[PDB]
Length: 238
Image (cartoon, rainbow, N blue to C red; front, side):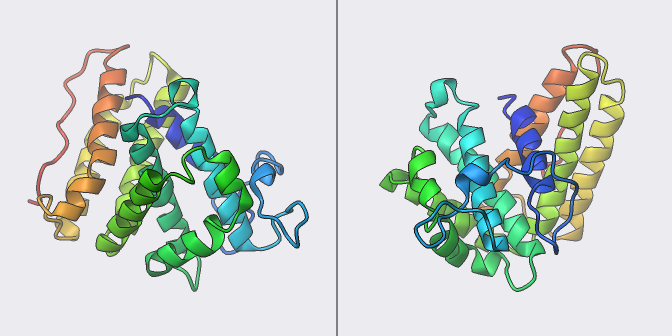
């Protein structure tokens, strides 16, 4: 679905607002953006004192926003799985950026900082479901199974998000869509080659739908205001 239009927008919004000194992607458009999701401090309302508090609140804000993409905020099993995967991919990227954190500390960070935030159980609809915990655990395990490629894979996802942002502003006149799609497929082919990615690996097959569905939707949307022959997404290392 055209879900990446919103996912890419929401991730950019939370990135600029993370307020963490060591991580800088931009200026916060709204200082109160995730304040509603800050963890409690000594039984009192949270203000987000630590970097872990801000990441935790930012992650919950993401999940809450992604669920809004579903009709009536009622996500199917497939939507819950897809949105948990996007949020946990972003979380892996953040932990990889943070010094003294990483994909190796992701499971620990989730249990000690996300499940620990009182706003996770009350605002994320599926938080208490055992089916949801299984989805989250699988996504965390997938990040660990692919830990060596996850930071570079995220850069490819970011390049895909840049095309979605361009389409969002140009609307029916994204004249550079074909040129950008060709640069994207070449950049992705280089990612497979440089990292010796076996696209038939079980773990890689479960993160690949983020790019394969995302790219397929993007070129279908560009071909709504133009008429171009877009290159197919690379299938293997070359």
